Image (cartoon, grey):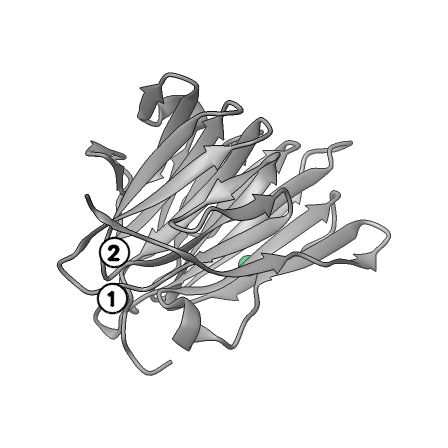
Amino acid sequence: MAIQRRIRRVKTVQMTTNSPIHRSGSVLEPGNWQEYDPFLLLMEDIFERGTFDVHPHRGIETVTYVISGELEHFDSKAGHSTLGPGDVQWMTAGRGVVHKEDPASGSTVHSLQLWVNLPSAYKMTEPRYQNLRSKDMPVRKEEGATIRVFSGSSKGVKAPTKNIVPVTMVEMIVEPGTTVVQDLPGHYNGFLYILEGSGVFGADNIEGKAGQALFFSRHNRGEETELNVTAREKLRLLLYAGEPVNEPV
Ligand SMILES: [Fe+3]
């Protein structure tokens, strides 16, 4: 029925040790806006308390998913918040904000940090912070799968998360042998990153396993497209797809 997306590339994350308290991996490398629009980068971090300093951002949004550990968030608009395993935060930097992500004492945080571009029209928007607890997100419940919607929608199940650039961000937990479908508008650009397990993906049943990012084929605006996911092992993954900004970076 719907146009079936393909996996156009499979990236295997190569982690490096930054310091005794910090390891990291590039999932989406920086400086390739033209391929990843609206995304600017996606970084995997494993870190302890004291790793990061306070830093400004402007003209972007950052989206953190905590895989494990307890994270303390600060920003200069909203102040302090916390995140635990499975939780997300969405920080719109806009005209400017400073932030710091710091693990709780004795905790090691494993996280995924996504940057989303802001279009010129919104680069100077007021900073805003959204704390997105896993338990508060809507979920598509299917036989053998749950699809938790952190942003955008999945088969009409819509997160209330405020977006500037429309972004669909979903967490899938899929039992072995179960097939799940994610709908995407044809002009969205996206990928998924596998946290746990393995499966086959897209029109050609391309294999993917934990620690890999699988990038989606591009289609036309106005087309209804779908991505098929079949678990082989117990599968946990994050899918990110968004509307390209299409502006010189
Ligand atoms: Fe930062």
Quick check: is the Cβ at mark 1 less than 8 Å away from ligand 1? no
Residue 161, compared with residue 13, is above or below; it is above
> Which quarter of the rendered picture does the C terminus lie within?
bottom left
The structure residue drawn at horizontal position 64% and vertical position 33%, both measured from the top left corner, is: 68
Percent from the top left, x then y, of residue 90? Answer: 40, 46
**Label 2, on which residue?**
164
* Cβ–Cβ under 8 Å for marks 1 and 2: yes
Tag 2's secondary structure? loop
Q: Is residue 53 visible?
A: no
User: Which of the two residues, 79 or 48, is positioned nearer the viewer here?
Assistant: 48
In the rendered image, which quarter is residue 137 located in? Answer: top left
Identify the residue at image location x=73%, y=33%.
Answer: 107
Q: Earlier in the sequence, mark 1 or mark 2?
A: 1
Q: Quick check: 156 left or right of 31?
A: left
- Residue placed furthest toward the right: 20
Instruction: Give the Cα separation between the discs numbered 1 and 2.
Output: 8 Å
Regarding mark 1 in the picture, which secondary structure is present there? Answer: helix
- Give the labeled residue for mark 1: 122
Q: Judge from the rendering whether residue 56 lies leftward or rightward of residue 165; answer left or right.
A: right
Query: In the image, residue 89 lies at what x, y percent?
Result: 45, 41
Q: Residue furthest left?
A: 222
- Residue 72 position within the rendered picture, expressed as x and y whole percent measured from the top left: 59, 38
Note whether 2 is above or below 67 in the view shown: below
Residue 227: x %, y % from top left: 35, 45
